[PDB]
Every structure is written in structure tokens, then in C-alpha cells.
Amino acid sequence: PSEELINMRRYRNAARKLIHHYSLNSTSSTEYKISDVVMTMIFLLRSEKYHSLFKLLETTFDDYTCRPQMTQVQTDTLLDAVRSLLEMPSTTIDLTTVDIMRSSFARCFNSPIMRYAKIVLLQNVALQRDKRTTLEELLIERGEKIQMLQPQQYINSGTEIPFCDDAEFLNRLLKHIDPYPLSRMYYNAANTMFYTTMENYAVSNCKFNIEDYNNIFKVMENIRKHSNK
Amino acid sequence: EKYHSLFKLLETTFDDYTCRPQMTQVQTDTLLDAVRSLLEMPSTTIDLTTVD
Image 1 (cartoon, each protein chain N blue to C red):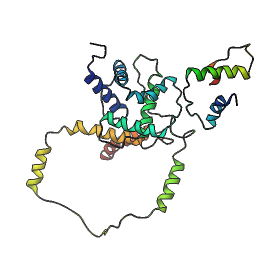
Image 2: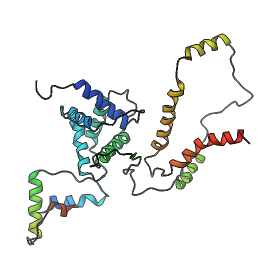
Image 3: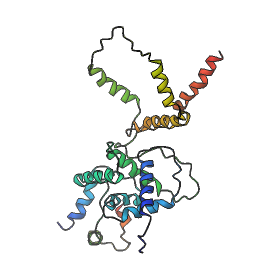
């Protein structure tokens, strides 16, 4: 009968939803209530566990994007409890994801802004450097060591091609495949690749992710032009 | 010796933009006191933000 008498299940599901969004960047959703952010925080604070994370998360409120200090052992227990409470299958959820989320929260309250916000703050400050370099230097630096590195395998590389011909089998496959609205289902996959395109770096990250990535899709219209001579 | 906790706290940030830890009531108060005690110019309101 205390105020804690709550849909803890609802609050859990919504906390997990929020984390799943902002951290894993999982998939399209409509995660557009400031309201239940509070429900999430209180769901945290109904334990000194997870409040342990909140100890760090509080530092958002001073809003300066200072690079967080590590106390190594406790940060390790932090990572532990993080993945645990997230109940994820230990998908290598690491310090980089952690600080990404930290910066997410260090971007949220930043808004005193209640009007609808079209603001995809793709950027992150905390890239362990004073300021962003170009990519060209890395095009030097990785290429060099790559040329230093030596092949991990041989290919026999003679004439080989595989094929199969069990037409009935293949049709059985087709039928099993039939239901899926792949049309829908794969756009999110493409978005996955997109996310990965910038997740690739927390390291002087590319600014011009935008318009050449868009040009890739313009290549479809280029294909239509090639069809139309 | 008097000022050493303060002193080392100032020293901390030889590396850029590290998060200086939070301090207890007592710590902050002795800090402000010692600040005034070295810079005994109470003509102005010695203040936290001065530290930042």
C-alpha cells in the first residue's frame, strides 16, 4: 500500500525498452514519453543495486561532459550488474556502450526543451581525444600495418563452383519461406548496417557520414538512368 | 602541510578534463575556509564557482 506499490513489471519493461533503444540502438519504436523516464529512474532507485550505476548517472546533472573516472574494480562490478540487470546474453556489452549511454543522458537533461525535438544528436564528445582528426591519416595508418600483416590462409583457388539441384527440396524451402513480409523486415536490417557505419568509430568519428551514404541510395536512380540510357 | 588536500585536488587535473570527485560537507567547508585563510581578502564572497 506504499507508493512503491507499483507495476514494477511495467517499470522494468519500460526501463529495458529505453536501454535497449538508446544503447543497443535496437530497432524502430515510438519511445517518445519523457514521463516514464522518471518511472525508470525510480525503478533504479528502488534498489541500492542499480543505484550504484545511478551514482555515475547523477553526474549528468552537472552537464559538463567530463570524461568519467574509473575505479577499476567497481567499474568491473558496474559492467557486471549492467549486463545482469539488462538480462542480455552477454553480447560483449562494454565500457564503450556504457559511456555512449552516459553521454546519451548527458544530452537529455541538457534540453529544458518540451517542444517536439527533431534532434538526432548522432555526435559524441567523449572520443578519448582532444579533437577529431581526418580519416586520411587513418587511411595511411591502418593500410600500412595491413600491408605489414601476412595471409592467414591459402585458397586452393583452382577452378571450383558449388551448386545444388534438389528442385523439390528448394521448393519446400520456398514454401517454408513464403509468409514473411521481408519487404518490411529488411529495412531495419539496413538500418542496422547504417548504425554500424558510425558505431564503427568512437574515434575522431567521421562527420560526413551523411550525403555520400545518401548517394549510395541515389545509385538506385543511377541504375534507373542506366536502364533509360 | 595545512593546505595539502586542497593542493592535491588542484593538482589532479594535470590531465585534461577529468572529473574531480565530489566532497563531503566537511571537506568542502574546510576547503573554503583554507581558501579564505590563504587568500584573506574577505572583501569579496569566496565562492565554489571560483573553483571551477
